[PDB]
Amino acid sequence: GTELDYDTFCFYYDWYGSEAIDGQYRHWAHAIAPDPGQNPGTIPGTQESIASNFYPQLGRYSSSDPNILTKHMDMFVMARTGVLALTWWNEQDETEAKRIGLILDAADKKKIKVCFHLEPYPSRNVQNLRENIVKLITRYGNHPAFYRKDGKPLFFIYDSYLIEPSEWEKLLSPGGSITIRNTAYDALMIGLWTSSPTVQRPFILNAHFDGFYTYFAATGFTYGSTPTNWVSMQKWAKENGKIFIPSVGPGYIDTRIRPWNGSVIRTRTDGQYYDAMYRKAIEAGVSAISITSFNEWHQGSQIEPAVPYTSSEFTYLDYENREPDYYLTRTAYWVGKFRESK
Ligand SMILES: OC[C@H]1C[C@H](O)[C@@H](O)[C@@H](O[C@H]2O[C@H](CO)[C@@H](O)[C@H](O)[C@H]2O)[C@@H]1O
C-alpha cells in the first residue's frame, strides 16, 4: 500500500527559476495574457506577487536546484506517482539539458521514472518531432530513470490536433515515410483527445496514435475532459487497441495570469472535486491515469504543497481546511484504489 504506481503519470513543469540557481525568478514572474490596445502588464515574481493564485510551500523555487528536486521526488513517493511526465519545449539550451539530467538523477534515487510531454514548440512538425524523439532516446534512453512500458518509451503529445493525421501517419503508421515503428526509436505515442467522437475517433485512428489523454484539469472544458464521457471513451479505446489515459486534477484557477478566464475556475472543495474526478477515471476501467498537475502553478491545478499567504499585493488561495500535503496523501489514496481495480 505504499509502493509507486508505474501506470500513474503526473505532469511536471521544469520552467521555474530562483535567484539561488538561475539568478532570476523565472515563471514566478509572468506576462499577464491579453483577453481574446490592452497593456495587461506583468506579474513581477516578487515574494509578494507571483504568477499563481496559490503560494508554494517551497517558495519561489528553481527547477534547477538539486535540493528542490530531491524534495519533489520525496513528494512523488508520498503521492505514489511512479512516472514524472516532464514538459519539453525544445529550448536547445544548456539550462534545459542541465535540468533534464538533474531531474533524471533525482528521480532515480527514489525509483521514479521520467517520460516526456512534447509541447507545441515553434514550427513543430513530424520531421523535427522524429529528430527530437531520436535525440531524447539517444541522450536519455540509457538513464535508469527513463520510463519504458513493455520495452517502449512513452510520449504525451500536447495539442496533437495542431498536426494533420496525414502528417502523423508518416511518423506513426508502420508503413509511414519516416516511421518510428519497428525502429530503435519506436515509442508509445499518446495524443490529446479534445473534441467530440465524430472528430476525434477518425483523427486518432488515421494518425496512428497508440493512445490518448485528455489533459485538462477543469471538468467540461472539452468533451475529453468531461468525465461522464470516459466510460464510452474507454470502450472505444479497447475496441480499437488504443490506450486511454484520462487526466484528473484537483481544481483549476488561472486568473492571476488570465484575469478574463474565470469561467474555467473549478473549486477544490477540500478535496471533493479531486475525489470525484479520480473516481470517474477508475470507474471507467482504464489501465493508466494521468494527473494534471504536479506543479502547473499558473493554472492552479497543482498537487504540490501550497501554504496560506497574504501579502501586501494579493491574498492567495490555499488548501485550508486541508494541510499543505493533503493533495499528495489523497493522491496516494486514489493510487491505491486504482491498483485495486487493475
Ligand atoms: O503542458 C501542456 C500545456 C498545459 C497548459 O494548457 C499550459 O501549461 C501550457 O503552457 C502555456 O501556458 C502556460 C501558463 O498556464 C505558459 O506559462 C506557457 O508559456 C504556455 O505555453 C502547456 O503547453
Image (spheres, rainbow, N blue to C red):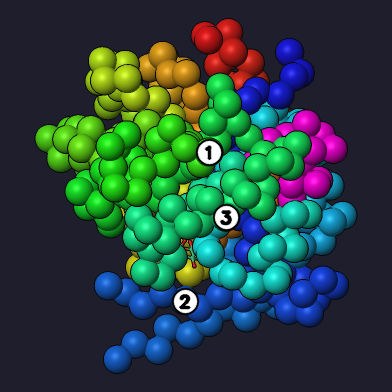
Q: Is residue 119 above or below residue 180?
A: below
Mark 3 or mark 2, whichever is nearer to me = 3
Residue 223, quarter of picture:
top left
Kindly identify the residue that appears in the image at 40 percent across and 35 percent down. Answer: 181
Rendering coords of residue 280 (x, y %): 41, 22
Kindly identify the residue that appears in the image at 47 percent across and 37 percent down. Answer: 183
Q: CA distance from mark 3 to mark 2?
A: 34 Å
The 10 Å Cα crowd at callout 3, few under 14, some 14 to 19, many 20 or more, is few
Q: Mark 3 CB in 8 Å range of ligand 1?
A: no
Q: Earlier in the sequence, mark 3 or mark 2?
A: 2
Span of residues in magenta: 103-114
- Per the rendering, the mark at residue 135 is 3
Tell me the residue that label 2 is attached to.
32
Q: Amino acid at mark 2?
A: Ile
- The residue lying toward the viewer, choosing from 336 and 7, is 7
SS of the residue at dot 3?
helix
Rendering coords of residue 260 (x, y %): 35, 68
Q: Is residue 100 above or below residue 6?
A: below
- Per the rendering, the mark at residue 184 is 1
- The residue lying toward the viewer, choosing from 186 and 214, is 186
SS of the residue at dot 1?
loop
Q: Is residue 148 left or right of residue 173?
A: right
Q: Amino acid at mark 1?
A: Ala
Q: Earlier in the sequence, mark 1 or mark 2?
A: 2
Rendering coords of residue 75 (x, y %): 76, 39
SS of the residue at dot 2?
loop
Rendering coords of residue 209 (x, y %): 33, 36
